[PDB]
Image 1 (tube, rainbow over the protein chains, first blue to last red):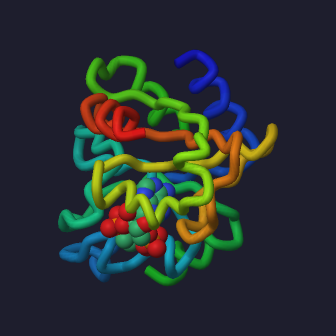
Image 2 (image 1 turned 30 degrees about the vertical axis):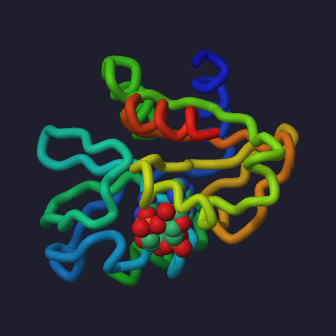
Image 3 (image 1 turned 90 degrees about the vertical axis):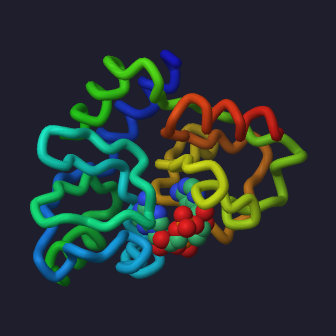
Length: 85
Length: 85
Ligand SMILES: Nc1ncnc2c1ncn2[C@@H]1O[C@@H]2COP(=O)(O)O[C@H]3[C@@H](O)[C@H](n4cnc5c(N)ncnc54)O[C@@H]3COP(=O)(O)O[C@H]2[C@H]1O
Protein backbone atom coordinates (compact mmCIF):
# COMPACT_ATOMS: atom_id res chain seq x y z
CA UNK A 1 0.00 0.00 0.00
CA UNK A 2 3.08 2.20 0.21
CA UNK A 3 5.05 0.36 -2.45
CA UNK A 4 1.86 0.33 -4.48
CA UNK A 5 1.76 4.13 -4.44
CA UNK A 6 5.42 4.54 -5.31
CA UNK A 7 5.08 2.22 -8.32
CA UNK A 8 2.18 4.35 -9.51
CA UNK A 9 4.26 7.54 -9.15
CA UNK A 10 7.13 5.87 -10.97
CA UNK A 11 4.72 4.70 -13.63
CA UNK A 12 3.09 8.11 -14.01
CA UNK A 13 6.54 9.55 -14.56
CA UNK A 14 7.62 7.21 -17.35
CA UNK A 15 4.35 6.96 -19.27
CA UNK A 16 1.97 9.84 -19.74
CA UNK A 17 -1.43 10.04 -18.02
CA UNK A 18 -3.81 12.44 -19.76
CA UNK A 19 -7.19 14.12 -19.26
CA UNK A 20 -9.48 14.00 -22.28
CA UNK A 21 -12.97 15.50 -22.67
CA UNK A 22 -15.81 13.43 -24.18
CA UNK A 23 -17.19 14.64 -27.51
CA UNK A 24 -20.76 14.44 -28.85
CA UNK A 25 -19.71 11.62 -31.16
CA UNK A 26 -18.78 9.60 -28.07
CA UNK A 27 -21.66 10.52 -25.73
CA UNK A 28 -24.42 7.92 -25.52
CA UNK A 29 -21.81 5.23 -26.10
CA UNK A 30 -19.87 3.12 -23.58
CA UNK A 31 -16.14 2.42 -23.50
CA UNK A 32 -16.93 -1.15 -24.57
CA UNK A 33 -18.90 0.29 -27.51
CA UNK A 34 -15.86 2.31 -28.59
CA UNK A 35 -13.76 -0.78 -27.76
CA UNK A 36 -10.88 1.46 -26.76
CA UNK A 37 -7.97 -0.78 -25.70
CA UNK A 38 -8.56 -3.21 -28.57
CA UNK A 39 -8.64 -0.26 -30.97
CA UNK A 40 -6.01 2.09 -29.55
CA UNK A 41 -4.01 0.23 -26.89
CA UNK A 42 -5.15 2.80 -24.32
CA UNK A 43 -6.25 2.11 -20.74
CA UNK A 44 -9.00 4.20 -19.16
CA UNK A 45 -8.21 4.69 -15.49
CA UNK A 46 -11.11 6.87 -14.38
CA UNK A 47 -13.87 9.29 -15.34
CA UNK A 48 -14.59 12.74 -13.92
CA UNK A 49 -18.31 13.39 -14.28
CA UNK A 50 -19.19 16.88 -13.09
CA UNK A 51 -17.72 16.89 -9.59
CA UNK A 52 -17.80 13.12 -9.16
CA UNK A 53 -14.82 10.80 -9.54
CA UNK A 54 -15.61 7.46 -11.12
CA UNK A 55 -12.65 5.17 -10.46
CA UNK A 56 -12.30 1.99 -12.56
CA UNK A 57 -15.34 2.87 -14.71
CA UNK A 58 -17.79 0.12 -15.58
CA UNK A 59 -17.15 -0.40 -19.29
CA UNK A 60 -20.87 -0.85 -19.99
CA UNK A 61 -22.19 2.48 -18.65
CA UNK A 62 -23.13 5.32 -21.00
CA UNK A 63 -20.63 8.16 -21.47
CA UNK A 64 -22.14 11.64 -21.14
CA UNK A 65 -21.03 14.87 -22.83
CA UNK A 66 -18.30 16.65 -20.89
CA UNK A 67 -17.07 13.52 -19.15
CA UNK A 68 -13.32 13.83 -18.65
CA UNK A 69 -11.55 10.52 -19.33
CA UNK A 70 -8.25 9.88 -17.55
CA UNK A 71 -6.03 7.81 -19.88
CA UNK A 72 -2.68 6.02 -19.95
CA UNK A 73 -0.75 4.90 -23.00
CA UNK A 74 1.89 5.89 -25.50
CA UNK A 75 1.64 9.43 -26.86
CA UNK A 76 1.32 7.99 -30.36
CA UNK A 77 -1.81 6.10 -29.25
CA UNK A 78 -3.34 8.90 -27.13
CA UNK A 79 -2.96 11.34 -29.99
CA UNK A 80 -4.73 9.05 -32.41
CA UNK A 81 -7.63 8.61 -29.99
CA UNK A 82 -7.85 12.37 -29.39
CA UNK A 83 -8.01 12.98 -33.15
CA UNK A 84 -10.54 10.23 -33.84
CA UNK A 85 -13.12 12.07 -31.73
CA UNK B 1 -4.07 15.20 -13.23
CA UNK B 2 -2.42 11.88 -12.76
CA UNK B 3 -2.47 12.81 -9.09
CA UNK B 4 -6.11 13.54 -9.20
CA UNK B 5 -6.29 9.81 -9.50
CA UNK B 6 -3.87 9.37 -6.63
CA UNK B 7 -5.56 12.09 -4.57
CA UNK B 8 -8.93 10.37 -4.82
CA UNK B 9 -7.51 7.03 -3.66
CA UNK B 10 -5.91 8.57 -0.56
CA UNK B 11 -9.13 10.19 0.68
CA UNK B 12 -11.37 7.30 -0.42
CA UNK B 13 -11.80 4.68 2.28
CA UNK B 14 -13.38 1.98 0.09
CA UNK B 15 -11.18 2.21 -3.03
CA UNK B 16 -7.46 1.53 -3.25
CA UNK B 17 -4.53 0.58 -5.49
CA UNK B 18 -3.11 -2.81 -4.67
CA UNK B 19 -0.22 -4.82 -6.05
CA UNK B 20 -0.56 -8.57 -6.52
CA UNK B 21 2.32 -10.87 -7.42
CA UNK B 22 1.57 -13.63 -9.91
CA UNK B 23 1.52 -17.16 -8.51
CA UNK B 24 2.08 -20.40 -10.45
CA UNK B 25 -1.68 -20.86 -10.18
CA UNK B 26 -2.07 -17.53 -11.96
CA UNK B 27 1.08 -17.81 -14.09
CA UNK B 28 0.49 -19.39 -17.48
CA UNK B 29 -2.89 -17.68 -17.60
CA UNK B 30 -3.83 -14.42 -19.32
CA UNK B 31 -5.92 -11.61 -17.88
CA UNK B 32 -8.51 -12.40 -20.57
CA UNK B 33 -8.55 -16.02 -19.42
CA UNK B 34 -9.32 -14.72 -15.93
CA UNK B 35 -11.55 -12.05 -17.54
CA UNK B 36 -10.73 -9.80 -14.62
CA UNK B 37 -12.66 -6.59 -15.29
CA UNK B 38 -15.74 -8.38 -16.58
CA UNK B 39 -15.78 -10.67 -13.53
CA UNK B 40 -14.70 -8.43 -10.65
CA UNK B 41 -14.86 -4.84 -11.87
CA UNK B 42 -11.12 -4.48 -11.28
CA UNK B 43 -8.90 -2.44 -13.57
CA UNK B 44 -5.31 -3.48 -14.21
CA UNK B 45 -3.38 -0.27 -14.97
CA UNK B 46 -0.02 -1.94 -15.56
CA UNK B 47 2.14 -5.02 -14.95
CA UNK B 48 5.56 -4.86 -13.30
CA UNK B 49 7.98 -7.03 -15.21
CA UNK B 50 11.27 -7.05 -13.35
CA UNK B 51 11.58 -3.36 -12.53
CA UNK B 52 9.84 -2.24 -15.71
CA UNK B 53 6.18 -1.26 -16.25
CA UNK B 54 3.95 -2.80 -18.93
CA UNK B 55 1.16 -0.24 -19.35
CA UNK B 56 -2.31 -1.11 -20.65
CA UNK B 57 -1.24 -4.78 -20.76
CA UNK B 58 -2.22 -6.93 -23.72
CA UNK B 59 -4.93 -9.16 -22.22
CA UNK B 60 -3.86 -12.14 -24.36
CA UNK B 61 -0.30 -12.60 -23.10
CA UNK B 62 0.35 -15.26 -20.48
CA UNK B 63 1.23 -13.95 -17.04
CA UNK B 64 4.74 -14.98 -16.06
CA UNK B 65 6.05 -15.76 -12.59
CA UNK B 66 6.91 -12.66 -10.59
CA UNK B 67 4.64 -10.38 -12.60
CA UNK B 68 3.17 -7.73 -10.35
CA UNK B 69 -0.36 -6.71 -11.35
CA UNK B 70 -1.12 -3.14 -10.38
CA UNK B 71 -4.84 -3.08 -9.70
CA UNK B 72 -7.37 -0.40 -8.94
CA UNK B 73 -10.97 -0.93 -7.82
CA UNK B 74 -13.40 -1.27 -4.92
CA UNK B 75 -11.97 -2.98 -1.82
CA UNK B 76 -14.62 -5.69 -1.85
CA UNK B 77 -13.87 -6.45 -5.50
CA UNK B 78 -10.13 -6.48 -4.96
CA UNK B 79 -10.52 -8.65 -1.87
CA UNK B 80 -12.72 -11.14 -3.72
CA UNK B 81 -10.27 -11.55 -6.59
CA UNK B 82 -7.38 -12.04 -4.17
CA UNK B 83 -9.18 -14.75 -2.22
CA UNK B 84 -9.92 -16.75 -5.36
CA UNK B 85 -6.15 -17.07 -5.82
N1 LIG C 1 -6.29 -4.01 -17.92
C1 LIG C 1 -7.34 -4.95 -17.68
N2 LIG C 1 -7.80 -5.05 -16.46
C2 LIG C 1 -8.77 -5.90 -16.16
N3 LIG C 1 -9.33 -6.70 -17.08
C3 LIG C 1 -8.90 -6.66 -18.37
C4 LIG C 1 -7.83 -5.73 -18.74
N4 LIG C 1 -7.57 -5.90 -20.21
C5 LIG C 1 -8.51 -6.87 -20.45
N5 LIG C 1 -9.12 -7.17 -19.43
C6 LIG C 1 -10.12 -8.16 -19.50
O1 LIG C 1 -10.13 -8.78 -20.85
C7 LIG C 1 -11.46 -8.48 -21.44
C8 LIG C 1 -11.31 -8.05 -22.85
O2 LIG C 1 -10.31 -7.05 -22.89
P1 LIG C 1 -10.09 -6.15 -24.20
O3 LIG C 1 -9.04 -5.16 -23.86
O4 LIG C 1 -9.59 -7.00 -25.32
O5 LIG C 1 -11.34 -5.30 -24.75
C9 LIG C 1 -11.96 -4.39 -23.80
C10 LIG C 1 -11.52 -3.03 -24.08
O6 LIG C 1 -11.28 -2.86 -25.50
C11 LIG C 1 -12.64 -2.17 -23.64
N6 LIG C 1 -12.41 -1.72 -22.34
C12 LIG C 1 -13.08 -2.19 -21.46
N7 LIG C 1 -12.73 -1.63 -20.27
C13 LIG C 1 -11.64 -0.71 -20.74
C14 LIG C 1 -10.75 0.22 -20.22
N8 LIG C 1 -10.77 0.46 -18.85
N9 LIG C 1 -9.88 0.90 -20.99
C15 LIG C 1 -9.84 0.70 -22.28
N10 LIG C 1 -10.65 -0.16 -22.87
C16 LIG C 1 -11.55 -0.88 -22.17
O7 LIG C 1 -13.86 -3.00 -23.64
C17 LIG C 1 -13.41 -4.38 -23.99
C18 LIG C 1 -14.02 -5.41 -23.12
O8 LIG C 1 -13.90 -5.01 -21.75
P2 LIG C 1 -14.27 -6.06 -20.59
O9 LIG C 1 -14.05 -5.42 -19.28
O10 LIG C 1 -15.73 -6.38 -20.70
O11 LIG C 1 -13.46 -7.44 -20.56
C19 LIG C 1 -12.01 -7.38 -20.63
C20 LIG C 1 -11.45 -7.56 -19.30
O12 LIG C 1 -12.30 -8.48 -18.56
